[PDB]
Image: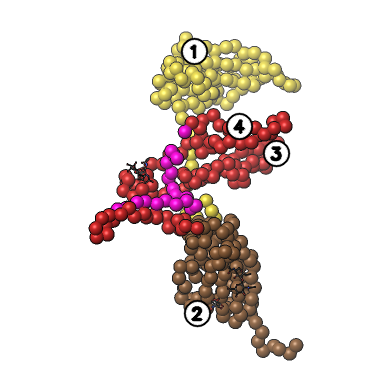
Chain colours: A brown, B red, C yellow
Amino acid sequence: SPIFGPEEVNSVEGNSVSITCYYPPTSVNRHTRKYWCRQGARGGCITLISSEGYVSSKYAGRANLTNFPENGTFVVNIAQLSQDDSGRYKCGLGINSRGLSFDVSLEVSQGPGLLNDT
Amino acid sequence: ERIVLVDNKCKCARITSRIIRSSEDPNEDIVERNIRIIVPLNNRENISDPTSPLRTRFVYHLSDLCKKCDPTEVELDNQIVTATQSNICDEATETCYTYDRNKCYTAVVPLVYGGETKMVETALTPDACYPD
Amino acid sequence: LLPPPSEELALNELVTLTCLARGFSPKDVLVRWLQGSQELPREKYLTWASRQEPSQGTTTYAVTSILRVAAEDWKKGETFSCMVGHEALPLAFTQKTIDRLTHINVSVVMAEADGTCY
Ligand SMILES: *[C@@H]1O[C@H](CO)[C@@H](O[C@@H]2O[C@H](CO)[C@@H](O[C@@H]3O[C@H](CO)[C@@H](O)[C@H](O)[C@@H]3O)[C@H](O)[C@H]2NC(C)=O)[C@H](O)[C@H]1NC(C)=O
Ligand SMILES: *[C@@H]1O[C@H](CO)[C@@H](O[C@@H]2O[C@H](CO)[C@@H](O)[C@H](O)[C@H]2NC(C)=O)[C@H](O)[C@H]1NC(C)=O
Ligand SMILES: *[C@@H]1O[C@H](CO)[C@@H](O)[C@H](O)[C@H]1NC(C)=O
């Protein structure tokens, strides 16, 4: 509920992206765990990259996550985007089964190919 | 589920309320009240380590959750007076069932260092106990 | 035929059962009481006479009768009845709806839903 970021995010294939999420700068909130997770269907809200050193197998070589405590912000970079990465995601702090999150929507569109006569 | 009356974090209990202006009989309406209890299955009785086994009994008194004893400010005539807000707050002393994200909880353990012993201090909730 | 009042079933001494017959055109009607399927002697209950019921347009008549029976018999579940006899009926038949017997509902739900809180 005190967590805020960009609600909708658009890009095309091959491009990069940069997402920023905001939190109150209290000292519990700076030292706690930050996470980026993909809220799929069928129950879970599986984590993709975290603040403690976890990077998933699908995000290897593509992503990182940086915590800036004096801003109260943390940034997520994701390179080499595809069309299977369209879905609903979440920022957050702490444990996933609580609700200190914020919903983000990401749509990736198909680029140009073999129609370039304009 | 509209207006919060009680948000207690020593017992982890939350009470909300809402006037549901119902459809049928449109000149009368109901008052709904929602209560939410989250019960921890691995906490101790006192919050220290070896106390007593895990708590298995949890008691909630709504006359204590709705209590209000901090002084307030009231403008009567052209004045500011201070008043109380409750009849029963003759006295912390309450027992807590859960932790709280914004408070430290520490302990003291004696360990040996070759010669004498010390009074080494140990953090029980490590996120909230950085000196900052 | 009416259930007993609640306050007479708190001293647990005796209970009262009231049989009301209402809205009939000729002014002659019998009332007989019976325990289970055996009848009672007519010196064990009180029955009134008939009167002109107040009504708009056309006239009716009403009659009443009561019975005081032991409280523990009604607490056990013995059945009482009422036999209202009349000339303008098919066979002058009875009605026996009283015995000693809140709405509870028990549900089990899987609730692997889309996304909600508690
Ligand atoms: C719940 O557990 C806590 C933690 O054990 C209890 O608080 C602690 O109680 C002990 C004994 O009363 C205190 O020890 C005392 O230390 C002073 C020196 O500071 C010494 O003069 C005394 O002789 C004794 O050794 C301790 O200070 C105290 N507080 C802590 C550790 O913060 C608490 O009483 C327990 N509560 C219930 C309701 O069981
Ligand atoms: C607070 O956020 C700002 C963004 O507006 C950060 O500024 C950028 O920081 C990066 C370092 O990772 C630099 O490469 C950029 O040049 C900075 N400016 C811009 C316009 O992007 C700033 O670093 C954050 N605060 C702290 C203390 O790091
Ligand atoms: C890792 O973070 C740095 C920020 O210093 C960023 O420039 C870089 O693109 C990131 N690496 C990726 C997204 O592979």
Q: Which residue is mark 1?
A: C45
Residue placed furthest toward the left: B115
Instruction: Please name which of the two marks, 1 or 4, marks the residue nearer to the observer.
Output: 4
Q: Which residue is mark 4?
A: B83
Tell me the tag on residue A61: 2
| Magenta-tinted stretch | B91-110
Q: Which structural element holds mark 3? A: loop
Residues behind callouts 4 and 2 on a single chain: no
Q: Given contact means CB atoms under 8 Å apart, are the residues at marks 2 and 1 in contact?
A: no
- Above or below — where is A116 with respect to B91? below
Tell me the tag on residue B26: 3
- Above or below — where is A98 with respect to C87? below
Instruction: Please name which of the two marks, 3 or 4, marks the residue nearer to the observer.
Output: 4
Residue A71 vs residue A51, the one in the foreground: A71
Q: CA distance from mark 1 to mark 4?
A: 67 Å
Q: CA distance from mark 3 to mark 4?
A: 40 Å
At horizontal 64% and vertical 41% (from top left) the residue drawn is B19
Residues behind callouts 3 and 1 on a single chain: no
- Is B55 placed left or right of B38 in the picture? left
Assess mark 2: CB under 8 A from ligand 3?
A: yes
Quadrant location, ligand no. 2: bottom right
